[PDB]
Image (tube, rainbow, N blue to C red; front, side, top):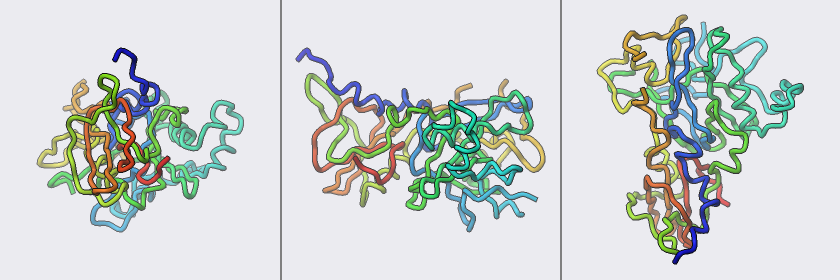
Length: 321
């Protein structure tokens, strides 16, 4: 049994630590200075298909522009109107806008949205490396730049916004994009779920079952993908204090308050809250028994099993191939 693992090249895109390298549920894998203070920001190299933000106890949608001039509770997370308008921007508008840039004009729509978002200067700071994240909506072909990079805020006494990341049927055409999304993501990142296939581990010439999985009821692929997402790699502080302090806000990915930057004397001037993509990122869904089998070790082969669909936290929650 001294031939190799024949699955190595095919399974590269499922090594999430390597190809994505950051949180998935909450991505805050880098820090970047703006006006003297280090802020956390998304840095995953792969698109996160189907991810959006749910605002608790409100009628506001998260792609609504932030409240300006408007009560805070009536606004979302998206860029406020700029002149000329930079967000939202359609795919056609983006390609026209970048007509004279050979290196950007013909990027795929997801990478283009990421790059477009990355051209927005934060807080008139000419030399900051901070770059806002974005959400691309594949139905309307619209790129939405996010002004708020925070993705979860729901401590006991934290809520003015209560919110959390989730996959929801309403978000199925959305993709969450960090500043770092690679231009060849289609080749090196997951997207489609693998029908009639089961993730496994290559041992001694056969694909064997993942040794340790956690099993949950799930009515379909979508709910399994949702469960994997909820348990996946997260850069959120696994710690909520008694009150939402400025230090905690920075730890959650906030940058601005009303008319000023958020600062804290407690900011150490690391790597305490970075998953670097480690987590329960993978699932095998049994379509015959309605069980979602979730695990936290990278798979290194596929098992030919017609009862299964293989999924990841990054993957689209519906699409199969």
